[PDB]
Amino acid sequence: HGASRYKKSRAKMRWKWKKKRTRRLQKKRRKMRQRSR
Amino acid sequence: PKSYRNYSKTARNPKRPFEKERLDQELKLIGEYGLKNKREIWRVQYLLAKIRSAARYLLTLDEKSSKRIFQGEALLRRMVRQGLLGENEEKLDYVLGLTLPKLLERRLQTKVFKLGLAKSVHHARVLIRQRHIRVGKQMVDIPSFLVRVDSEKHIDFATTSPFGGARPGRVKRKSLKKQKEKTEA
Amino acid sequence: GSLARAGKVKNQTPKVPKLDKKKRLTGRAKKRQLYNRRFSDNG
Amino acid sequence: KGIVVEKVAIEAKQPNSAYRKCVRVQLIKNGKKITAFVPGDGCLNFID
RNA sequence: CUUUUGAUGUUAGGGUAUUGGCCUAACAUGGCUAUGACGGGUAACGGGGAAUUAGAGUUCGAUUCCGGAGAGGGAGCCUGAGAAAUAGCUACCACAUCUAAGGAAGGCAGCAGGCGCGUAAAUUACCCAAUUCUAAAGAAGAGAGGUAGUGACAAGAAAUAACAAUGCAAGGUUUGUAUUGGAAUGGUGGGAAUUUAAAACCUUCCCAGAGUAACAAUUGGAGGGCAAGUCUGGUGCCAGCAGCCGCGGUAAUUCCAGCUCCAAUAGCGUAUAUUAAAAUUGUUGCAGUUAAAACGCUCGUAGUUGAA
RNA sequence: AAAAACCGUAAAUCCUAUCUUUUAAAGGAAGGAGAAGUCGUAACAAGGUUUCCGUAGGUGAACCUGCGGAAGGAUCAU
C-alpha cells in the first residue's frame, strides 16, 4: 500500500528487498519494452 | 393508460420478527381480543401510530396557532366521534394516551359480545360472518368495522336472521320430520 | 473424479409415508388452541 | 440460460473434506464460460 | 480552447413574419477558461414525482399528465392558415413483396397477432352505450376511448368453525381438554329480479345445498443470529447441509428420513438491483501517536475565514 | 412542357487519418489458489550477526555488504 508499509508483525519478507526485486523486474521489463516498441 | 384510482397499503411490517417479549405480549393481546391473525393487529398499530404522529406534529406548534386550533380540534372531534376519548379527556396528552385495548374496544366482534348476544368472542366473530346482525336499518358482516358512540345505541340482531322471526330453522330437518309425521298419520 | 456416488444417501435411506393424523386446524381455531394451551392451563 | 457441457468434480477448503459436483456452462446471452454448483444430492444425474 | 470553412464585434445589405453572422461584402481582433471551458463516458428524454425518512439526505423517474424528438437513417419538396407531415410525395443505401420478366407498389416505435431476442410480458374479442373529437355538426365515423378476455405485477376485505352435555387436568363449583348432535352459514349446482349497446360479475331472492363440515392450506426451518428437539430411525469425511461461525472419521441436537413443534399465512421461499441498518462518506455526524491515514520543511496566488 | 446552366440545399459510394469498444497471437514475465513435493534458516527471544529504513553493488533463495539514518531496542540512568 502506501508509505505505511513494513510493520513486520505479520512475519513477512523484508520490504526493502521486496522493493529491490520489484525494481529489478521494472528494469528488465523496461528493457523488453524498449526492445519491442 | 393507467386507471386513475389511488391505492396504498394499510399494515406495516414490524421488522425484527423474533423478539420473545413482544411476541408473547402479542399472544396475550390476541388471546384477550380474539382476532384472527397478526396482520390485523399490525394495521391497528399503524392506525394508532399515525394518530400519535399527528398528535406530535400538532403539539410541536405554538399556542393560539391557527394550524393547531384547526387540525387538532378536527382530530379530537374525530376521536370523540369514535368514542376513544371520553368527556373528561380533552387535551393533547390525553389524545396521545391511546392504547391498544382502548382502540380494540370499538370493533364489532368485541362490541357485540360485550353487550350480549353471543356466548364466545369467536362465536360472535362467526355470527358476524354469518350476517345475523344489524347496526340499525343496515346489516353488516365485516368484523373490522368500527362503531361510533351513538352507533352503539341501536345495535341488535338482523331483520332477516332466522333467530329474529324469519324462516324458522333447518329446512332439511323440519321437512324430513313433517314427511315422517304425515306418513305416520 | 469419482462422481458415481451422487444421491447415495437419498437412495439408501428407507421410505415411510406420513400416516393419517388429524386435519390440522386453520383460521382462528389454531390461534385459540395455542392461546388456551399457553396461558390458561399452565401455572 | 446456458448449455451444460461437461462434468468435473471440484474440491473444497482444507478444513472441509468432501467433493462438490460442479458443472461448466456456456452462456448464450454473452458467450462465456461459468462454473455452477448443482444443488441436491441426486440432481447430478437428474440433468441431461 | 474557438478563429482560412463565422470564431467575437462594428458598418451596410439579402433573407425571413419580425430581430440577429441567419447569410453576403468590408473592417476590427477578438470571445470562453481550476467558480473545471474545450473534450470523453452515461447499460442518460427533462419536470412536477416514486422508494426510504427521527431530521438531514441517497437512490429510481420509459411509464395516467405538461413539454421535446422521431416514425429505417440521413436529405429534399408541394399543397395547405398551420407539416420540412410520413396510414403526403421525391431520391440513396440496407431490406423486402408481386411480377406474364416488360414493370409496379412498401414501411406495425397505431389497435391485434407472427418471427427473432432474451428470464421476461395479455385477444388477429365487442362497441362508439360513457368521455370527447371531425365535418356540410342530432340520426355518420372515432383500435382516441369504454366493456369483455388472460392475468398469485402489486393492493384491500374475509371462510377452512362456533355452541350444550359427559369423562381428564388444573382450581375453589371456573377454564381448556375425546366422545356424543343438533342449531347456523358460507362454498357449489340451478332459477329468477336488477345490471349492461349485448353478454358477463357483483348485488337480492327461491330450490337443492356441510360431520372425517373428503367442501382438508401450505412454504421454510427446529446448534448459535433465531422463535422453536442431546426426540426416534438410515449414512458415517461419503452423500451432503450451511447467507457467516461452521456439522459430518459409529449417540450426527446441523446430512437423507418419521413424530412433535415452530414463524408466515392465501401466502412464503430463490437471485440480482436498492434503501435503512451506515455515526463504515459522516453539513448537524467519522478518523489521522501506536489500527487505514498530517505532504520533508517553508514562502506563496486563486479560495476560505478576519481587532474593537 | 420536356430539356439546359447557374450560385444553393445536399442524399449516397470510396479513399485518408484519428478516436472509441471487444478479440487473435509463437513466447516472455507476474499474481492467486490448490496438494503431506524439493532446497535452505531468512524473520518472532540478545532468534542465535539486534531489528528496520533510504540508496548502490553482489549472491541459487530466503538474503549480504558499503554509506547516512530511526528505536517501532536489547539502554528512559555518574
Image (cartoon, coloured by chain):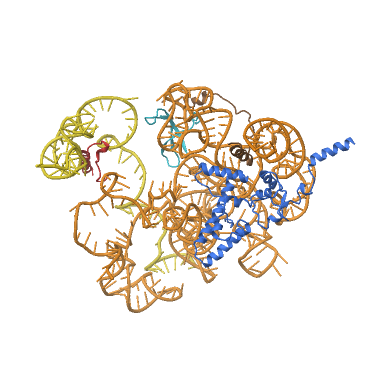
Chain colours: A red, B blue, C brown, D cyan, E orange, F yellow
> Which quadrant: the N terminus of chain B?
bottom right
In the figure, residue F49 lies in which quadrant?
Answer: top left
Residue lying at the far right of the rendered structure = B185
Residue E79 in the image, given as x and y percentages of width and height: 53, 69
Q: Is residue A16 visible?
A: no
Image coords of residue C42 (percent x, y) = 59, 36
Q: Residue at horizontal 61%, vertical 43%?
A: B31
How many marks do you count on the picture?
A: 0
| Residue B106 seen | yes
Residue E23 coordinates in the image, percent (x, y): 36, 70
> Looking at this view, is E91 or B163 the one in front?
B163
Report whether D18 appears left or right of B135.
left
Given residues E250 and B48, the one toward you in this image is B48
The answer to whether residue B114 is above or below residue B94 is: above
Q: Is residue E95 left or right of residue B76?
A: left
Q: To which quarter of the image does residue B137 belong?
A: bottom right
Quarter the C terminus of chain B occupies: top right
x, y (%) of residue E131? Answer: 63, 63
In the picture, residue E170 is in which quadrant?
top right
Relative to E291, residue E73 above or below = below
Nearer-the-camera pick, E305 or E168: E168
